[PDB]
Image (cartoon, rainbow, N blue to C red):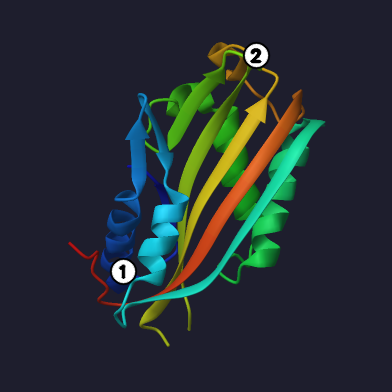
Amino acid sequence: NVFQPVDQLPEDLIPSSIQVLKFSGKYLKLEQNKAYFDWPEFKTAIDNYTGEDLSFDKYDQSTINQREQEVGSMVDKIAKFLRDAFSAVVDLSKLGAIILNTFTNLEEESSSGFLQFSTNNVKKNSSWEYRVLFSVPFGAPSYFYSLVTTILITADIEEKTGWWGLTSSTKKNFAVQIDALELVVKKGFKAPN
Protein backbone atom coordinates (compact mmCIF):
# COMPACT_ATOMS: atom_id res chain seq x y z
CA ASN A 1 0.00 0.00 0.00
CA VAL A 2 1.22 3.51 -0.91
CA PHE A 3 -1.23 4.90 1.65
CA GLN A 4 -2.10 3.33 5.01
CA PRO A 5 -5.89 2.79 4.92
CA VAL A 6 -8.02 3.62 7.96
CA ASP A 7 -11.77 3.57 7.59
CA GLN A 8 -14.77 3.33 9.89
CA LEU A 9 -17.00 2.83 6.87
CA PRO A 10 -20.07 0.57 6.58
CA GLU A 11 -19.44 -2.51 4.43
CA ASP A 12 -21.12 -1.19 1.25
CA LEU A 13 -18.65 1.71 1.09
CA ILE A 14 -15.25 0.07 1.48
CA PRO A 15 -15.12 -0.73 -2.27
CA SER A 16 -15.53 2.93 -3.31
CA SER A 17 -12.95 3.78 -0.67
CA ILE A 18 -10.47 1.29 -2.14
CA GLN A 19 -11.10 3.07 -5.45
CA VAL A 20 -10.03 6.33 -3.81
CA LEU A 21 -6.85 4.62 -2.60
CA LYS A 22 -6.25 3.42 -6.15
CA PHE A 23 -6.77 6.94 -7.53
CA SER A 24 -4.55 8.62 -4.95
CA GLY A 25 -1.92 5.93 -5.36
CA LYS A 26 -1.44 6.89 -9.01
CA TYR A 27 0.04 10.20 -7.92
CA LEU A 28 2.86 8.70 -5.92
CA LYS A 29 6.13 9.74 -7.57
CA LEU A 30 9.09 7.37 -7.65
CA GLU A 31 12.43 8.94 -8.60
CA GLN A 32 16.00 8.80 -7.30
CA ASN A 33 15.01 5.56 -5.55
CA LYS A 34 12.67 7.49 -3.27
CA ALA A 35 8.88 7.64 -3.39
CA TYR A 36 6.95 10.74 -2.39
CA PHE A 37 3.40 11.79 -2.96
CA ASP A 38 3.01 14.19 -5.89
CA TRP A 39 0.73 16.80 -4.33
CA PRO A 40 0.72 19.36 -7.22
CA GLU A 41 -0.21 16.73 -9.81
CA PHE A 42 -2.85 15.28 -7.49
CA LYS A 43 -4.44 18.67 -6.83
CA THR A 44 -4.52 19.18 -10.60
CA ALA A 45 -6.11 15.77 -11.11
CA ILE A 46 -8.68 16.81 -8.50
CA ASP A 47 -9.40 20.18 -10.12
CA ASN A 48 -9.61 18.65 -13.59
CA TYR A 49 -11.91 15.88 -12.36
CA THR A 50 -15.48 15.79 -13.66
CA GLY A 51 -18.00 13.28 -12.35
CA GLU A 52 -20.54 12.98 -9.55
CA ASP A 53 -18.86 10.31 -7.45
CA LEU A 54 -16.00 12.53 -6.28
CA SER A 55 -15.92 16.08 -4.94
CA PHE A 56 -13.31 18.45 -3.49
CA ASP A 57 -14.06 19.78 -0.03
CA LYS A 58 -10.94 21.52 1.27
CA TYR A 59 -7.18 21.17 1.47
CA ASP A 60 -5.03 22.31 4.37
CA GLN A 61 -1.29 22.49 4.92
CA SER A 62 0.95 23.38 7.85
CA THR A 63 4.73 23.49 7.78
CA ILE A 64 6.54 24.14 11.03
CA ASN A 65 10.23 24.83 11.42
CA GLN A 66 12.60 22.96 13.77
CA ARG A 67 11.42 22.79 17.37
CA GLU A 68 13.17 20.88 20.11
CA GLN A 69 10.25 18.80 21.39
CA GLU A 70 9.00 15.37 22.41
CA VAL A 71 7.25 13.03 19.98
CA GLY A 72 4.00 13.06 21.95
CA SER A 73 3.92 16.84 21.97
CA MET A 74 4.47 16.78 18.23
CA VAL A 75 2.08 13.97 17.29
CA ASP A 76 -0.50 15.69 19.48
CA LYS A 77 -0.23 19.03 17.69
CA ILE A 78 -0.50 17.16 14.38
CA ALA A 79 -3.64 15.38 15.61
CA LYS A 80 -5.12 18.64 16.92
CA PHE A 81 -4.38 20.27 13.58
CA LEU A 82 -6.25 17.54 11.72
CA ARG A 83 -9.28 17.30 13.98
CA ASP A 84 -9.80 21.09 13.92
CA ALA A 85 -9.41 21.47 10.16
CA PHE A 86 -11.42 18.48 8.97
CA SER A 87 -14.95 17.29 9.62
CA ALA A 88 -13.80 13.80 8.63
CA VAL A 89 -11.90 13.81 11.92
CA VAL A 90 -14.19 14.29 14.93
CA ASP A 91 -12.25 12.08 17.33
CA LEU A 92 -8.75 13.13 18.37
CA SER A 93 -7.65 10.12 20.43
CA LYS A 94 -7.93 7.42 17.75
CA LEU A 95 -6.01 9.80 15.51
CA GLY A 96 -3.07 10.74 17.72
CA ALA A 97 -2.80 7.06 18.62
CA ILE A 98 -2.36 5.87 15.05
CA ILE A 99 0.30 8.48 14.35
CA LEU A 100 2.14 7.86 17.63
CA ASN A 101 2.19 4.11 17.00
CA THR A 102 3.62 4.51 13.50
CA PHE A 103 6.46 6.68 14.75
CA THR A 104 7.15 4.59 17.82
CA ASN A 105 7.26 1.44 15.62
CA LEU A 106 9.03 2.86 12.57
CA GLU A 107 11.64 0.10 12.49
CA GLU A 108 8.96 -2.50 11.80
CA GLU A 109 6.72 -0.54 9.44
CA SER A 110 9.91 0.72 7.76
CA SER A 111 9.26 -1.51 4.74
CA SER A 112 5.60 -0.59 4.29
CA GLY A 113 4.75 1.31 1.13
CA PHE A 114 3.27 4.31 2.96
CA LEU A 115 6.55 5.43 4.49
CA GLN A 116 9.57 7.10 2.87
CA PHE A 117 12.96 7.70 4.44
CA SER A 118 15.83 9.86 3.20
CA THR A 119 18.89 11.69 4.46
CA ASN A 120 20.44 15.10 3.88
CA ASN A 121 24.18 14.69 3.28
CA VAL A 122 24.63 18.45 3.67
CA LYS A 123 22.29 19.12 6.62
CA LYS A 124 23.29 15.95 8.51
CA ASN A 125 19.68 15.12 9.34
CA SER A 126 16.96 12.84 7.98
CA SER A 127 13.23 12.71 7.41
CA TRP A 128 10.21 10.46 6.92
CA GLU A 129 7.04 10.73 4.86
CA TYR A 130 4.05 8.92 6.30
CA ARG A 131 1.06 8.49 3.99
CA VAL A 132 -2.33 7.60 5.48
CA LEU A 133 -5.89 7.78 4.12
CA PHE A 134 -8.95 8.37 6.35
CA SER A 135 -12.48 7.41 5.31
CA VAL A 136 -15.65 7.91 7.37
CA PRO A 137 -19.38 7.97 6.51
CA PHE A 138 -21.54 11.10 6.39
CA GLY A 139 -25.08 10.40 7.64
CA ALA A 140 -26.88 10.66 3.20
CA PRO A 141 -25.78 7.04 4.03
CA SER A 142 -24.38 6.69 0.50
CA TYR A 143 -21.63 9.29 1.03
CA PHE A 144 -18.30 9.40 2.85
CA TYR A 145 -15.18 11.46 3.44
CA SER A 146 -11.65 10.63 2.31
CA LEU A 147 -8.74 12.49 3.83
CA VAL A 148 -5.68 11.94 1.68
CA THR A 149 -2.91 12.68 4.18
CA THR A 150 0.88 12.97 4.27
CA ILE A 151 3.05 13.86 7.25
CA LEU A 152 6.71 14.72 6.78
CA ILE A 153 8.85 14.62 9.91
CA THR A 154 12.43 15.87 9.90
CA ALA A 155 14.90 15.66 12.76
CA ASP A 156 18.52 16.14 13.76
CA ILE A 157 19.02 12.41 13.34
CA GLU A 158 21.80 11.51 10.92
CA GLU A 159 21.21 7.74 10.98
CA LYS A 160 18.07 5.88 9.98
CA THR A 161 18.75 3.69 13.02
CA GLY A 162 18.45 6.91 14.99
CA TRP A 163 14.68 6.72 14.46
CA TRP A 164 14.44 3.21 15.93
CA GLY A 165 12.83 2.90 19.36
CA LEU A 166 11.16 6.29 19.61
CA THR A 167 9.01 6.88 22.69
CA SER A 168 6.30 9.44 23.43
CA SER A 169 8.74 11.46 25.53
CA THR A 170 11.72 11.19 23.17
CA LYS A 171 13.15 14.66 22.49
CA LYS A 172 14.60 15.89 19.17
CA ASN A 173 14.75 19.04 17.07
CA PHE A 174 11.63 18.20 15.02
CA ALA A 175 10.36 20.02 11.95
CA VAL A 176 7.07 18.93 10.39
CA GLN A 177 4.88 19.44 7.33
CA ILE A 178 1.28 18.24 7.19
CA ASP A 179 -0.60 17.98 3.90
CA ALA A 180 -4.24 16.96 3.93
CA LEU A 181 -6.98 17.04 1.30
CA GLU A 182 -10.59 16.20 2.09
CA LEU A 183 -12.82 14.69 -0.57
CA VAL A 184 -16.53 13.90 -0.47
CA VAL A 185 -17.12 10.54 -2.13
CA LYS A 186 -20.35 8.93 -3.31
CA LYS A 187 -20.87 5.18 -3.24
CA GLY A 188 -20.04 3.92 -6.71
CA PHE A 189 -17.00 6.07 -7.38
CA LYS A 190 -14.35 4.52 -9.64
CA ALA A 191 -10.68 5.44 -10.02
CA PRO A 192 -10.48 6.84 -13.60
CA ASN A 193 -8.34 4.53 -15.78
In the rendered image, the residue lying farthest to the left is 193
Question: Would you place residue 80 above or below residue 90 in this image?
Answer: above
Find disc 2 in the rendering and name its residue: 124
Question: Would you place residue 111 above or below residue 149 in this image?
Answer: above
Give the image location of residue 180, x and y in percent. Answer: 55, 57
In the rendered image, the residue lying farthest to the right is 68
What amino acid is labelled 1 in the image? Glu
Image quadrant in which the N terminus is located: top left
Find disc 1 in the rendering and name its residue: 11
SS for callout 1:
helix
What amino acid is labelled 2 in the image? Lys
Give the image location of residue 20, x and y in percent. Answer: 33, 62
Mark in front: 2 vs 1? 2
Identify which residue is drawn at 33% across, 72% down: 49
Q: Would you identify the image quadrant in which residue 163 lies?
A: top right
Q: Is residue 107 left or right of residue 159?
A: left
